[PDB]
Length: 505
View 1 (cartoon, rainbow, N blue to C red):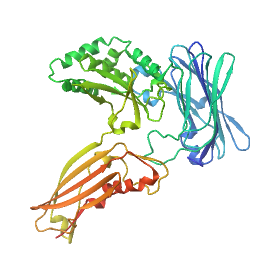
View 2 (view 1 turned 135 degrees about the vertical axis):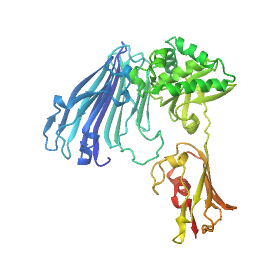
View 3 (view 1 turned 90 degrees about the vertical axis):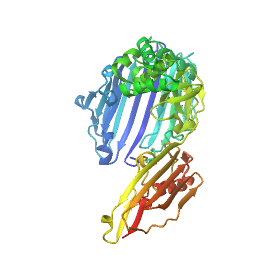
View 4 (view 1 turned 45 degrees about the horizontal axis):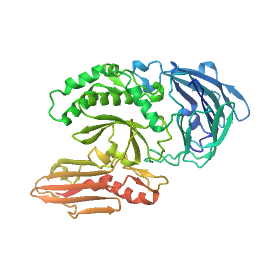
């Protein structure tokens, strides 16, 4: 955690060579102050690489104890394994994760690790960086450096920090570096924004432009003929009446028959297996699945394109593919676009920047999720023999009740972000036993705030009672000044007492 550990130094250096080979060199000094720190995953380092094009070189690995004793990491403390993300995915079974087990740890000891990943020509189309510089512990000093051949275009930016680039050329190489000091630990608060704007990140690219990066990806995606995938798409949708049915057939076929293999694009050199091979294998990376769906939709007569989703604060003219957070597919159905992705693009809407692979920015609308459910509840005179029956109306699962927000802190230091806007209505039909008397007031309960509202109405109807609960949340992000108002809404919804009906017998 925070005063549990500190990175005294971090240094990261990226180099692009004229032949297209790269080096990434990472060194760190990490002091652990508690057994909690020492016994956590801070006891290890994890280094992922693709040995088909990369080699890992450990420059040094040791622990320095407070008294000056140096404990060099022994050979048997280096263990190579398959990264968990590649499990059960045969095409990626060459991928490696080196686990360095830090030895000689004691209270106040400092871990030193310095390594490079060397990438041979022909694997990465460009130098393409999106590096988080904030850690879960404070970083006293962080040095980052990018070197490319003179004449190579370079766009770079340090986001979430005012530190200025220092430019240095030498020996036909153009170098830029930054030095950040005293980077605070990230906050442990839940529900911070998916993209934290004040969290320092280095983003850089040697593609000619962001658009060129996307066009390069597209060209590579289109390199396989996808003959079977196209023919299959046509066979699958030849009967269908309307365009929507065709989209559903294709989407459902893919959803039902391919599992998603979460292999980062960097670990595939930013490309895909041959698309017909993806289709036959029944697993695919997000990128592979996106292209398969796109190829099949287009073959079926549904004009479609792959979309890249970036954080909303980024200058997408100046970044490469490393800054992409999600992929989606746009399908035009009877002149109206719809988006296909694991989570709806309209949940976050304009929080993010969405760009097609042909380079067009898309102003995605922000659309509330709509939940409407019903429950029936019987109450017996059994349950009220001892004077009273406490009827807890059951909570539903979908929507805000699944957000993990039933115990929100009253204090908040960081922005608070909801997964989506939302509107929910839950109608309970309650049938109490004969002669049970409702003790709960039938007066409507309403809490209304600037960015939402929660209501409860209770209406006896014959020998049933209808209870309607509603919530609407109409803003996604909240400053600490705004947090109390949205917290009171969310709490009005989730507080179990607010679902109780009391009856006397």
